[PDB]
Length: 107
Length: 107
Ligand SMILES: CCCCCCCCO[C@@H]1O[C@H](CO)[C@@H](O)[C@H](O)[C@H]1O
Ligand SMILES: CCCCCCCCO[C@@H]1O[C@H](CO)[C@@H](O)[C@H](O)[C@H]1O
Image 1 (cartoon, each protein chain N blue to C red):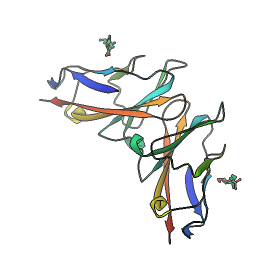
Image 2: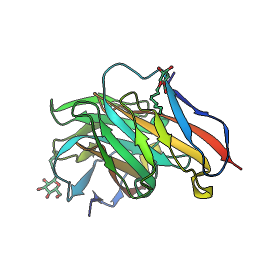
Image 3: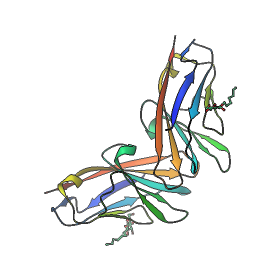
Image 4: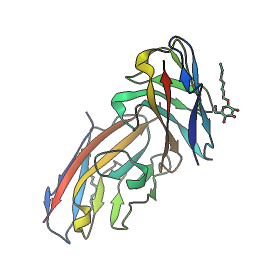
């Protein structure tokens, strides 16, 4: 089962957090991260294609995030606006996609 | 701007409806249709890989739908359960994705 978790879970303003990703499925094309609890184009942070290793920003991209080839997302110089939920959609080769939501809490 | 519309808009129970799709972006991996107004894995009707022209059913597939290469969705022998909103997500080759919602009304 695809899941994500934040390290750390409670994050001091101005520090760093890594969203770790567990149990990627076999046979995927790539990753799409979104701010909030659902898949929503208007809140897309980044898209990443695992075949070319290319990252492309979406409308909610801050410039402070880095995605890794295993879909883990690093956020640096974390702000109040970064707090709360994130949603990872994994795009499967058959287009029957999977999603996981995680969160962290800025203080 | 990606949009969809139903032909016909008001559809008699037991007849047929075609969801037409306008203004697909270029450079696409595939299409995913969902029942309702959002992208939600539990309500996915079909996923379609453009590279192979191959359709795979999701959990909401009824067996009465057919999807075409330009993302149009035909539904035959329409039921009451088919009424209302449908959402199409288009997966671009950069994994920055677009969605459009439409509806039809069964009587
Ligand atoms: C600056 C730190 C760079 C982070 C590099 C990628 C870290 C990813 O690390 C990987 O995380 C996966 C999800 O993250 C976990 O499932 C794995 O245990 C781990 O191998
Ligand atoms: C019974 C068989 C149904 C025919 C399925 C193919 C119909 C595809 O529908 C398409 O929607 C587009 C909207 O831009 C139009 O521009 C295309 O020309 C139209 O054919």
